[PDB]
Amino acid sequence: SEVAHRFKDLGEENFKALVLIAFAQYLQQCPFEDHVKLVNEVTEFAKTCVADESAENCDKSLHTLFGDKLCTDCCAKQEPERNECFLQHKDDNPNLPRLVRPEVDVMCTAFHDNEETFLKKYLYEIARRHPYFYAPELLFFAKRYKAAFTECCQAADKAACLLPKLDELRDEGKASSAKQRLKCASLQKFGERAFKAWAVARLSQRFPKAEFAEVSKLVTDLTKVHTECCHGDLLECADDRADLAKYICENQDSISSKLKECCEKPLLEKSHCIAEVENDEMPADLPSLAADFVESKDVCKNYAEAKDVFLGMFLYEYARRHPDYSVVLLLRLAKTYETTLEKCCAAADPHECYAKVFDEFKPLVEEPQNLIKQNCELFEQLGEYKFQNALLVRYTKKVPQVSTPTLVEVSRNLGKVGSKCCKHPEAKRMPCAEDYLSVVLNQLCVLHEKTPVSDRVTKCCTESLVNRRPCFSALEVDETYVPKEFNAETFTFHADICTLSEKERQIKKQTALVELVKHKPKATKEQLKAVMDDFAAFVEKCCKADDKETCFAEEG
Amino acid sequence: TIDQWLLKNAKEDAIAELKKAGITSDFYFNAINKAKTVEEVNALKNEILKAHA
Ligand SMILES: CCCCCCCCCC(=O)O
Ligand SMILES: CCCCCCCCCC(=O)O
Ligand SMILES: CCCCCCCCCC(=O)O
């Protein structure tokens, strides 16, 4: 009945599309024709399972169905567990190339040759390069993908039209996927309670006129959606998403006023829209938290009776008043309150003991404020590229044991905060910045974890989800790192740099910059700025040569 | 229609349920009472029950 249930709830195309995503993410190293085959042949099966409900095997338990269809060490394995085998071997940075789209004519030709297979392939491709991509947003991006070819492919300049559309699509996906990766990490490494806490903070910021009870609703159901989704149960995930949008669009009256337009849309666009909506205006006059959370004779009695809800309401009340705080900051405040109550409700005079909690929050607020402010001042003076260069040095000097690819990827991403967030008024900056940073640090953590080389990084990735950013920013330079010996090769460049995009070309320059810092970690600062200027110059020199480009050898 | 009647009825009742589990504070009963939607009464009530044990 379950596989009928889902087909009935989702529709052919969505059902179809998601199961293909499912397999991709389970089985990353297997071809498109395999994957497609077993999707139709579970889809033939489903179609029957609807019409008479009770066919021999329509009984079966969803994993079981997909688990059986894949095989044709994990297929030897027994159940409630064989499934766990899959999401285990689900790994981050795959063992796969870059897509590097072939050509606009090549594609539109293929696009026409099969509208469907083509579009079915995009899903497959993204699906398999990010195995935690949030399935239901993927469908959304697909419709955006299909729309772009269904517009530009007829034009005289297919290229001037299609590319800009596709590139903002690529970027939108990378953002979406990392974002999801952090939700899966929170759940899977720090547990449900943490995620729930995150969700109370975000939803309270975003739905501040909602009562707590409606926020419990959203969080409990949001948490299922992500539990299931992160756990590969993509249909039940996708349908629960639909249900929650259903519940949200029916009780707008009592969540937010900013939803009518979202809630006037087709399914795929609806959730996505809702997921991204402006925080609502908070209610006009909100009492201070003092009464409930410090002055009441009953703080400890209330806390003892139901700690997590008590802290929950605390987090709800703080957050709904503080759209300007990042989510992680908020969680640190709740954590602070919590450890104060755990200390103070033991005391002879609890009240005395916690009278001054609110004072503890100030330095905790100040700290991210001050930091972002510095980094934005720096970005302002440097531009994106040199700002990334500054971070590379900083991070490489902090954790030089981390691999070079990783440091480049992560530092470039940290640098993109400044373009993202310094733009805004210092008042929307913190949520924008600190929450993007979280996501980037997460990427670092998950990459690092597959080959732990640095105890400092492991430690920061592990002690505390919400303090990762402060923890990493607190790292001083690793003055005990032994510099690796020199390879005059990693610091030569070859003629093919010339023919690469500025960005790829940048990635080389930054790769060399990191390598140099590892080799001479002590000598630094102006030198390092001056090194990039030279790099970014005998390139733009050697390439203008038209002198057999051997010139690069002749700077070696 | 009238889900208000159900709303009224779910609040009364959740509160009895909580009371039966030994929750004793209006802080929580007030919150149930602020609810606005039956689904939320339910989720809030269950989170309290989970939180108490
Ligand atoms: C630090 C706060 C702990 C929050 C986890 C419990 C919140 C779930 C939503 C709710 O309270 O109904
Ligand atoms: C973020 C809350 C928005 C609720 C809309 C349902 C799907 C959201 C995905 C997500 O919330 O992570
Ligand atoms: C009081 C809210 C704290 C967030 C919930 C998870 C707490 C333990 C993990 C951590 O923060 O490192």
Image (cartoon, helix red, strand yellow):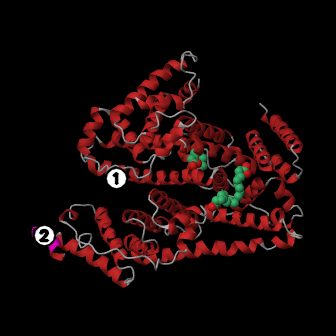
- The residue that mark 2 highlights is A550
Image coordinates of residue A39 in percent, x first then y, are 42, 29
Assign the C terminus of chain A to one quadrant of the image.
bottom left
Assign the N terminus of chain A to one quadrant of the image.
top right
Amino acid type, label 2: Thr
The residue closer to the viewer here, A141 or A352, is: A352
- The residue that mark 1 highlights is A164
Left or right of residue A66, residue A531 in this image: left
Left or right of residue A389, residue A533 in this image: left
Residue span colored magenta: A545-553
Task: Please rate how many residues cluster around mark 2, counting C-alpha atoms within 10 Å: few if below 14, some from 14 to 19, many from 20.
Answer: some
Location of residue B49 (image quadrant) = top right
Image coordinates of residue A238 in percent, x first then y, are 55, 38
Residue at 53%, 70% in the rendered image: A472
Residue A550: within the magenta?
A: yes
Task: Please rate how many residues cluster around mark 1, counting C-alpha atoms within 10 Å: few if below 14, some from 14 to 19, many from 20.
Answer: few
Residue at 88%, 52% in the rendered image: B26
Whether A138 is drawn above or below A355: the answer is above
Secondary structure, mark 1, is helix
Residue A491: within the magenta?
A: no
Secondary structure, mark 2, is helix
